[PDB]
Length: 48
Length: 493
Image 1: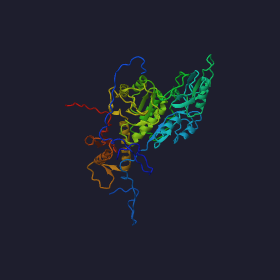
Image 2: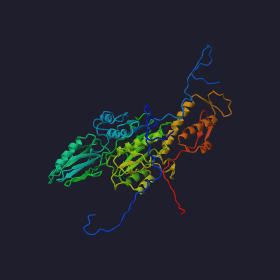
Image 3: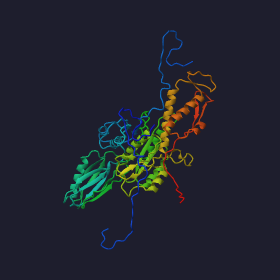
Image 4: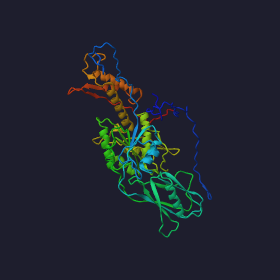
């Protein structure tokens, strides 16, 4: 038996049921996005 | 030789006689229909009599049958929007002692921002168009008219005169359609993002103090019936109701009644109260989710959680409820959510947790039963996972069906008996092989992991004292759910 999600085992309506499963979809791993954080100072009249 | 059912033995008439028997006519187990019973409260119309179970099928029918803006109307509406396939039953609880007021909303100030004011009463957005130079009395009147224009709210409203020096000031008194400990609702404002209240309003909510007692579920649990009622929704949290339902389920979950029931609850409050409750109850047949500062009332979260839990468990009893989400439920605001340490501490205490993933979606995290202490103190992990009790219930259901169908009217005997091929005889060895084959039958579909240790530890014997019962002792060998991944890298360079 295939482990289903959102397809109850207690269904008896004869209409077909198709399911889209997001697991086992991405192969490899996505490249991380660069995140850089700088601890600077702000002078006077700075609006931040 | 063969024991033929309903065929007259000792007959002479020459003909052909053919009979159909249901013994050995079912493979695996039939799919158990999921059934959910809620112990909610009803008022106003309340056409259905209190303490009477009603098979409700739609939100409109619930509103017309349990009164508009009642606890059960909202709870059934929330459930049916999450799990339509399940069979639902509602039992009204009449009225609870206490007071019929929630609080007051103070709305003072004049505004000049041609914007809108949004109030999240019980999580249902109420938007009022605030115009330039609008006194607070106009906003109060428009807000109360809007509240009366949305009967789905569990709270009615009436505008009250200021009776004070401030002319613009005006308040909206709130009454609850049902009187109980769950009557209080959050009247927060400026939830979500991208919208701001106008400049010239001072908004406050003075919640009237009180301890309205929940109605007693005394005849309600006596009027349930005999249906299995796999999962039960309890909005109440006071000790008497939970103790009474604990007795009810323990009678059901006993080895003779053979009915299985699980209670799902949600507690809104602070972290300390949740910890105290989880330490207090100490029961393996109830599970609670703790929420701090829920904009919506607790019973809605309980209903949706029970719906998704019933779905996940009926589809696969041993599948962990880690990534399941509660659809359409408003999460607590940021800065009022338990961190990782708080969630771990709560999971230790016994109250289940939940994760608020990105996108304003509330997940399930770990549903755990409120069982932490063995009989003589100690600490027993044999019932932590709700998957454990659910799979135990499913296993008992399947084996009861198999034994009651495959071996009716048989005649057991000692192992060395010379029974014929078709004769209805079940020696301990025959039952042992049948149980092993059935164990494989629910091993192909998971839920029992190991098999060898089950075979060695399986012990089917004839009762030496008295007769006509097989003493069967089997290690459960329940499967476990992939919950925590621990990995040490130990790079070698």
